[PDB]
Image (tube, coloured by chain):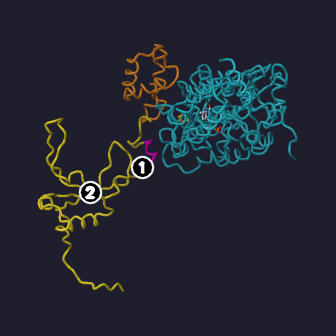
Chain colours: A cyan, B yellow, C orange
Amino acid sequence: PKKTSFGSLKDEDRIFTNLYGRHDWRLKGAQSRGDWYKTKEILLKGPDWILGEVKTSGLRGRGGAGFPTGLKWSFMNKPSDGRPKYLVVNADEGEPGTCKDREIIRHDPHKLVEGCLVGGRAMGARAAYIYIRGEFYNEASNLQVAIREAYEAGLIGKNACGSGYDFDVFVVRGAGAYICGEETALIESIEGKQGKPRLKPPFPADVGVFGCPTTVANVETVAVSPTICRRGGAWFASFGRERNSGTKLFNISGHVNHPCTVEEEMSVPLKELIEKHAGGVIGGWDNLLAVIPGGSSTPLIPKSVCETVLMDFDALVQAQTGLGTAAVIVMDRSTDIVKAIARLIEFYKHESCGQCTPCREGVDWMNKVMARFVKGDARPAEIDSLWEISKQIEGHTICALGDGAAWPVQGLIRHFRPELEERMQQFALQHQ
Amino acid sequence: TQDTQLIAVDEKLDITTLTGVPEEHIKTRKVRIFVPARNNMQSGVNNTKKWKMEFDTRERWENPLMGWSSTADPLSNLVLTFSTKEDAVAFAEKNGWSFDVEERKVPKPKSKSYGANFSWNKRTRVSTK
Amino acid sequence: EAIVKNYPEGHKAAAVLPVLDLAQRQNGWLPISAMNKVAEILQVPPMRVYEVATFYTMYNRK
Ligand SMILES: Cc1cc2nc3c(=O)[nH]c(=O)nc-3n(C[C@H](O)[C@H](O)[C@H](O)COP(=O)(O)O)c2cc1C
Ligand code: SF4
């Protein structure tokens, strides 16, 4: 029936077999693992079949989105109007804590390119636009020698795997901006213009890069696709829970003994995750003061909720936060949470593309007022003003960077108002 | 139903002599009605939703003292509002001023779509946002 | 040329990111003359190059 507990994912069941670079990341090791198996049959089975199994597996957005891959990829099943349908894969990973895409792409790029081939066959896409964050130079260099090897083997290109589907991959650099992780900002960046997100509609589905029908995806999202297609949706549906199913490549960092990134089955309580893999938070479980879940965009969670809540989108929503990209960052007692959120929102201010008014102005306003808070120069009233400003930012931005910068402030206020109050009281007392 | 000894009076009102306007101000002056075009410096619209009447501008000389803007015609800074142009023209004729008519220019509704900012082949694709 | 052929024709200014980065790869710091040269190479207005040069990270203008 229902799996009573989740955790200790089977080693052979881990999708990223070379996550730690223990295997040949080129074609030979990839085929030894099982990459590029039964591709011919996968393309022959058809986009309808691939879309059926992607629904059966039931992948919520692995790139911190949450939207099911089923309907998102079904948006590219309408007959072609003549414009060249494309597939796009996002690999920005500028999010504080995001390290899984870089690791997989420098260790298992062949699985990624096989996800692009199979996915694009499902998508009706002419080729893939695999966009790599410009800081990851050697990672892109590795993925593209892998791509060249695949082209030599004939797996990707004209008549891919002897199927007639003329899919291709284009390796795209990016001159560096976290806003480029946003799907429409990604469209704009790869279009040679600024990395400013566009307003939807027109959705990325009908109108994408160069106006052609496209669809974005995360590196992990498409990378897990070929393995689950070969195995079937049952493998992914078995692990994890309902809705939030399968596996997610968790990243662990912060004040832990072993700040590692590991693959583990889905919907696992944090209590096991930090202790068994990361060697526990430095100073024991008692020393743990707070934990931010996947992505700094998701509000931080006090230790009173992390030990019980599982790592699944719905449960983190119940935990007044989000699952994000499984970038669990832990802060111990010695950490100054106020200054940590200070540096975090300073990063957000540095990353704002400035298009829409709410982000461009409110994030800077938050930076200044909250730095004053960190120092302690404030009256107890300004906490409510900061909360209201966080509400103002939310929902009025073209892209979700505004929401992702407003949420940490909301979490900080809600979970540590008295710490702020005592900080500012000490500031009032020290000066006379 | 409203018996007050009613009488058919076909010719239009001649309240001119009643208004007390001097002869040359009622004869020489020419008044035009129009919808005032919005200030292009502004995007606000609710100033071109009425029919205003104004009179021909007259001599504006500078007084010897400070070079002020002394004038002679009293009906210079006089503008009258009206809901519809029919009321304005009726007022103009019944008062007796020679009137000029300009039709209410309104913006043509143009098809606008954000999807035009991007294209696959159309020239309308933008180059910056 | 390799960067240009990667992208569909008609929309060629989209390649303005690597080529200008390529300029870095041969010069590091990018003079205004480098931006103008990239603009004339890609047949794109010069300020459309200036915008992407001044909006993204790296791309050291000094
Ligand atoms: C500011 C911002 C940054 C983002 N950065 C990333 C990113 O680095 N990687 C990513 O996969 N998605 C990122 N996203 C989410 C994308 O907009 C998009 O929803 C996502 O790539 C879809 O992933 P999926 O196909 O796995 O559902 C970002 C969104 C925003 C608003
Ligand atoms: S929130 Fe608005 S201003 Fe900020 S990066 Fe997104 S689109 Fe640009």
Badge 1 crowding class, 10 Å Cα cut-off, few under 14, some 14 to 19, many 20 or more, is: few
Q: Is residue A116 visible?
A: no
**Is residue A310 shown above or below A370?**
below
Residue C20 counted in the magenta span: no
Question: Which three-letter amino acid code belongs to the residue tagged 2?
Answer: Phe
Look at the numbered disc 2 and give the secondary structure of its residue. Answer: strand
Q: Does the magenta stretch include residue B113?
A: yes
Q: Quadrant of ligand 2?
A: top right
Image position of A228 (left or right of C47): right
Q: Nearer the viewer, mark 2 or mark 1?
A: 2
- Look at the image and give the residue range highlighted in magenta: B112-120
Query: Camera-side residue: A22 or A219?
Result: A219
Q: Name the residue under label 2.
A: B34
Q: In which quarter of the image is residue A268?
A: top right
Q: Position of residue A80 (x, y in %)?
A: 52, 48
Q: What element carries label 1?
A: loop
Q: Identify which residue is drawn at 42% across, 49% down.
A: B112
Relative image position of residue B82 (x, y in whole percent): 31, 61
- Left or right? Give the position of B1 relative to A156: left
Disc 1 marks which amino acid?
Answer: Lys
> Which residue is pictured at 40% across the width and 22% down the height?
C38
Q: Which of B46 and A45 is in front in this view?
A: B46
- Ligand 2 has an atom within 8 Å of the beta carbon of the residue at disc 2: no
| Residue position marked by numbered label 1 in the rendering | B112
